[PDB]
Image (cartoon, rainbow, N blue to C red):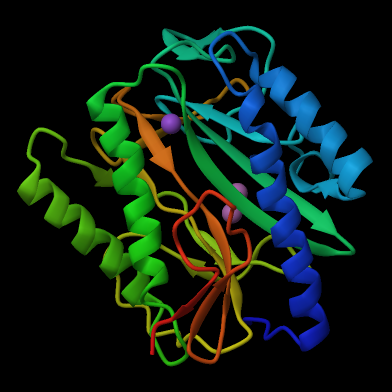
Length: 279
Ligand code: NA
Ligand code: NI
Ligand code: NI
């Protein structure tokens, strides 16, 4: 059952989404070669708890051992902040940022019982053209999906729009060909982290109709190689590309408006409007 938020819930979700964006704005100057993901987790936990008077959701309700998810390079999602690089058998489980890395920081804040969920890519020092393209095309996927959202649109149009963009990029850029992760989806979000509906990022024909007052996440994960992932059996959380190529993701929490959508997690650096009129 999908929740339609009332005026009061929308204003609390607006506050939680602004707070989630603010964490990502605050952390940026700390993100550089030689910093551990553990340090970023400490800086974010202190800011969320002591400055924002909010809660980091992963730590408190999801059984996650830390306050933020930090996914580097071939990590797709749910990277665990740590003070040292470890190994999942022969697979690197990184925690220390190096020149050339891409980094996803995923933030989920609760403020007065409502969730704000968002993530972005950081480019660490001199990043390859390949890796810049991957991060840039992943954000184009999110932006283009957002431009399809308005009351009356079927949910399947989101993944169809993302897969159309990736098929177009693959036709026009066969040196930089990408795939869409199938294992993880966007979701209704509000008083509860995981609400209806599920939002897949690949071509599908889900007939669920978007309505004004629905709030959900769009969070496409784009792989530089094949679509498949592998779960870390040792730490229960770290998701790797099955082929060891890099993966990039961007996430926004969005409110369906009368004529389009509101990006509740929009950041100050983004050249996307806070409110899209898609009618
Ligand atoms: Na990645
Ligand atoms: Ni998230
Ligand atoms: Ni999410």
